[PDB]
Image 1 (cartoon, chains in turn red, cyan, yellow):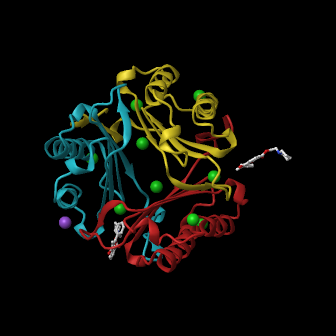
Image 2: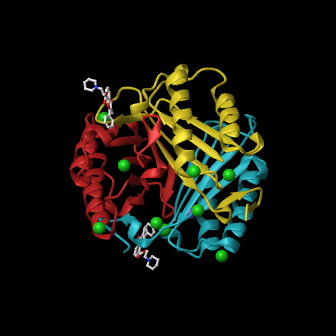
Image 3: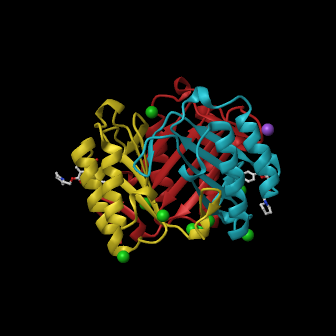
Length: 114
Length: 114
Length: 114
Ligand SMILES: Cc1c(-c2ccccc2)oc2c(C(=O)OCCN3CCCCC3)cccc2c1=O
Ligand SMILES: Cc1c(-c2ccccc2)oc2c(C(=O)OCCN3CCCCC3)cccc2c1=O
Ligand SMILES: [Cl-]
Ligand SMILES: [Cl-]
Ligand SMILES: [Cl-]
Ligand SMILES: [Cl-]
Ligand SMILES: [Cl-]
Ligand SMILES: [Cl-]
Ligand SMILES: [Cl-]
Ligand SMILES: [Cl-]
Ligand SMILES: [Cl-]
Ligand code: NA
């Protein structure tokens, strides 16, 4: 799986260890080994949400399976909680798009997972 | 909805008010409230279009519904017009990918829209 | 088509000519004219893969058609090979998501490809 967070919060406010925390919490949440979890945080972005440039986060989670109605509600509660505690972004300013990828459409290690 | 523009034009060439114009014009085009709209502009990117490093943009619009053949033609005319007028990017050096999101695949405020 | 690479490799380690090499190789691989190939490289990113900050890449290829089981295996060998040769990223630290776009969902030049 791959989790990407784009945010207007400054780089210095991303705590040391945040990528590791995302890696471990997503490995547990998705039930996949951490070897397969990639995370990417992009601070200092020029963005607005609802017309306001107060702190916000625009995110995506792509996974081969482990995506669905109940699972995504669980991920949204987990990820909003982490972004609130660690980046001080209010949960009503976190927006997450979820993607269930087919294995044939994910490349890795010179081939694909199909 | 979420609208992202990635471009090689420099940050200083992004005029004041640009995120607000995107929010307001996308609210009218999609019919969605400005409250639900996120906009994100990423200048100074290392990009080429058609083998050329002249000004270009790669963009995406994600929305729960309000995506379709006629609507996407209308969005493309609106958004290329804004990128030409405000960033001086030729419309034939702009790509916009459109994504009709299922409500269950959009998280916000500790939940999803399922 | 559009190919995007996000990587933690520093900008100085992206060799001269890399975007042009990607354009030409993807034009041949997808069978589309180079005029239609857009490429975007994002170095210096804050990313982890498998819990490690060793060099890695998260990429996507979007194309109207020319996406499939066999084709995506071929693209993955080609692109992992380029990332290993040119950016020194191990293929087991690369993900590439593939997107077969409907023509109506790709905007260009004030309209769409539909
Ligand atoms: C930001 C925000 C959003 C929103 C966030 C991200 C993306 C989209 C919207 O939805 C909301 C919503 C709500 O339900 O938006 C969507 C539900 N909607 C039902 C019918 C079909 C289309 C989807 C309600 C109150 C405040 C809000 C709100 O303050
Ligand atoms: C992410 C990552 C992965 C990996 C990614 C997804 C799934 C599985 C692994 O494998 C690796 C590997 C590796 O799997 O190598 C195999 C050889 N290995 C040699 C020594 C004895 C055991 C076998 C090596 C280095 C970095 C890595 C590495 O950074
Ligand atoms: Cl995955
Ligand atoms: Cl970190
Ligand atoms: Cl589920
Ligand atoms: Cl939406
Ligand atoms: Cl339509
Ligand atoms: Cl969806
Ligand atoms: Cl295409
Ligand atoms: Cl195929
Ligand atoms: Cl599509
Ligand atoms: Na506004």
